[PDB]
Image 1 (cartoon, protein in one colour):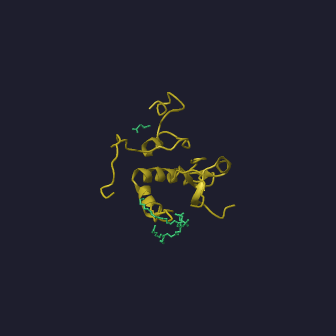
Image 2 (cartoon, rainbow over the protein chains, first blue to last red):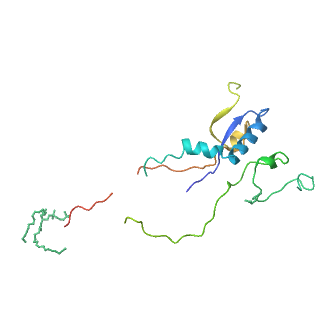
Length: 49
Length: 51
Length: 46
Ligand SMILES: CCCCCCCC/C=C\CCCCCCCC(=O)O[C@@H](COC(=O)CCCCCCCCCCCCCCC)COP(=O)([O-])OCC[N+](C)(C)C
Ligand SMILES: N[C@@H](CCC(=O)O)C(=O)O
């Protein structure tokens, strides 16, 4: 079973004038289905099982 | 609305982080993953049409 | 150190790293898992 359920983030420095708009452009891409596009084309392949 | 109107300083609960809310309230790191899922009553289940 | 302005990689959000850098909201929710090495053995009709 999965443990230490911490996700993947974009790292920026403490100042990071882009910190707020990067996160807002990541929540937006989850809702738009853009990340489901990326999961389909890069993660969900299922060669054999 | 309570945090936006400064009636409270926190909104601990089952709030999901999203676009519109993050532009009026400052969320923290998620403590549990959620999303949108579909719950369907089970269809019992059958044998394959080519068993 | 200033070499990079962003880390676009599978960087896990941690308490240790969060004290020095600003992580974004996760673009991928996941966890830790263990990977291990993976028909019919009917010898004959007898
Ligand atoms: C559904 C039930 C209803 C029907 C029932 C019918 C009644 C049956 C009637 C009679 C049977 C009488 C006894 C003889 C049977 C062999 C026994 C034996 O010791 O063989 C050995 C050598 O056998 C082989 O390894 C070869 C068998 C397959 C190839 C065919 C060669 C001829 C064998 C037959 C010649 C024809 C004889 C004709 C005259 C009788 C077994 O080798 P093993 O390595 O120990 O095998 C273990 C099994 N294992 C590999 C899966 C682990
Ligand atoms: N938990 C959701 C509401 C429930 C839902 O509609 O899925 C929220 O904070 O807005």
